[PDB]
Image (tube, rainbow, N blue to C red; front, side, top):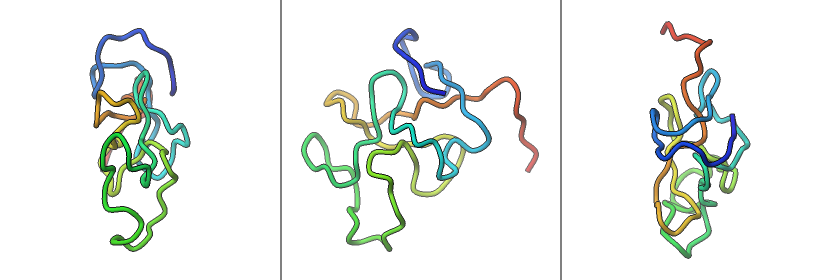
Length: 102
């Protein structure tokens, strides 16, 4: 989990940083994504329109810019603060330990 710049890439098999269990299971608290990007606080309208602000959706409970995803899958998928991305995967990757059955 977490890390610094080193891998010239990202998205699943692009950047380092391994996850555990369900990277997008309402966990993490890293508020980061990859090696120089965040989740973009859902409300900070400046670089890019994050998404349906806490007015249309049933106020689920987004942790500001805490790298995460609305529903689920395996890894989060939210924009970043860096005005040169608009989208990035949280610093979480398949670790060579945990497995998956269901």
